[PDB]
Image: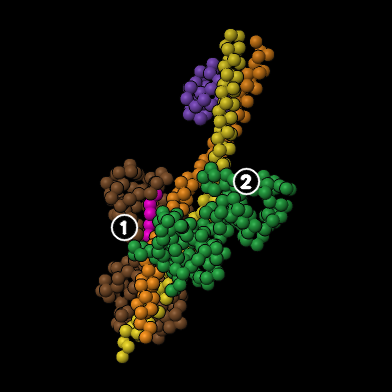
Chain colours: A brown, B green, C orange, D yellow, E purple
Amino acid sequence: QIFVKTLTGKTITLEVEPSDTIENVKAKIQDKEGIPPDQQRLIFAGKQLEDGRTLSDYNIQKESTLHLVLRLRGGMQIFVKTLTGKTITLEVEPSDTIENVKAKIQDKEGIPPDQQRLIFAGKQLEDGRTLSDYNIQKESTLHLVLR
Amino acid sequence: GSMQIFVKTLTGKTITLEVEPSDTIENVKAKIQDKEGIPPDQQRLIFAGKQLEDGRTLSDYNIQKESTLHLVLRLRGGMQIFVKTLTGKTITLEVEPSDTIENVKAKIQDKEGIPPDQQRLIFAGKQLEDGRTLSDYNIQKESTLHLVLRLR
Amino acid sequence: LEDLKQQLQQAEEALVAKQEVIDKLKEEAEQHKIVMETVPVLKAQADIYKADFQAERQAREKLAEKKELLQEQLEQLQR
Amino acid sequence: LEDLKQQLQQAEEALVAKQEVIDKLKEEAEQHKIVMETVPVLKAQADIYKADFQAERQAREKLAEKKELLQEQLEQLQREY
Amino acid sequence: RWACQSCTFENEAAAVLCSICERPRLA
Ligand SMILES: [Zn+2]
């Protein structure tokens, strides 16, 4: 149906029959590119779009390109303190598993998810255990250490 | 006067300046803190497709007479301290250590709408009186002030 | 008759020249139009990153608050 | 030799016309270029606002440091014995 | 009677331009 560019980076294309909703457009992007909904803002004809107002609303049909701007800030940033006291931030979602979180730490600090080991509120965390499954509120601090 | 230049924000807000053959960049931001009062650290200046660094001069990146410079307002300055009203509201301010308290209070006015006559600042126990700079009361960055009110 | 013929062949040889310059200006105009489209986007990019820089500030405010309310629960316990 | 004249007067009615259009494409091209000078600036504006959001993050990153340091000093002073 | 080698239209020899393209004889 429709095309999408990423700040003169990648091009994508999507199937959505265009009575489709903005959140369920962004989701079909998080499918393609794994960039979390909250961290993209979509633009047509100079203007940004909102969740409630849909594709049919802004009169957007076939082969029509859509410009994508990567947001910087996430929904739900947390923290990581260490022994040294060197302090880091992550951007994540309540649905994200720990095997996932570690890979983001590796991304910034270059250390493998094999050796990384995380602790919160007197409890060592194992993986495939969502953040709701460790009662992680927003702006939590996880103590972390090596093996 | 040997020469002059023009300087624009993003809108139509055009200004003009007096600068010699070769004055350093910080000096030009300082002539802006002399016509617009925007602190040096809160501006970055652009020519061609490039920003202009602090240490270097105008002769060095080719500037001839009555060329234009594009100006972008930064979003935050060197220092930020905090102010905690008895309401249970804490708001944030932008400063530099050389800034006077009468300066600071005028910024509190600008956000909460209350005049610096009927204001007083206090820090870690004891009373701030004015003229004196932030550096002169030993105010660290991300250090917090309590605030309270006066009459007449 | 056949002296005016000499100049109506230059006249349409001039239309050829003129068109050629039309073509190039149009061709060109379009290459520049590609770069003029990004503009509207970048203007937005700015005003996303902005509202976000703001959003981070408001996260700080509310943290630094917690911290002053702690350095008064520790300012009491000094016996 | 009525069409021959009628067509040299139609010919240059056209070469005036196609000049006037070439004038408005040039005039245009100019303005086009004055919109193309903003882009270098806006590409910066982005990268400033960015680097700022960063330097603000770093501030917030570090504050949290102070904040366990406080909560931890108040787990220390809370168990007075 | 010529065909404008842009839109290939059977045009009158009388016309210096196209009836569609505003485009000359020789291009
Ligand atoms: Zn034709």
What range of the chain is rendered magenta?
A: A39-43
The reply to whether residue B124 is visible in this rendering is yes
Would residue C17 be found to the left or right of residue D64 on screen? Answer: right
Check the image and name the residue furthest to the bottom. D81
If the image is split into quadrants, where does the C terminus of chain C sit?
bottom left
Disc 2 crowd rating (10 Å Cα; few below 14, some 14-19, many 20+) is some
Most prominent secondary structure in the magenta stretch?
Answer: strand
In the rendered image, residue D79 lying in the magenta stretch gets the answer no
Would residue B90 be found to the left or right of residue E14 on screen? Answer: left
**Callout 1–callout 2 Cβ contact below 8 Å:** no
Q: In which chain is the residue bearing label 2? A: B
Q: What residue is drawn where x is 63% and y is 21%?
A: C11
* Image x and y of residue B3, in percent: 71, 47
If the image is split into quadrants, where does the N terminus of chain C sit?
top right
* Image x and y of residue D27, in percent: 58, 33
| Mark drawn on residue B16 | 2
From the image, tell me which residue sits under label 1: A27
Q: Amino acid at mark 1?
A: Ala
Nearest the viewer among E4 and C26 is: C26
* Image x and y of residue D68, in percent: 38, 78
Q: What residue is drawn where x is 43% and y is 72%?
A: D63
Q: What residue is drawn where x is 47% and y is 25%?
A: E20
Q: In which chain is the residue bearing label 1? A: A
Q: Nearer the viewer, mark 1 or mark 2?
A: 2
Q: Amino acid at mark 2?
A: Thr
The reply to whether residue C61 is visible in this rendering is no
Q: Is residue B51 above or below residue D31?
A: below
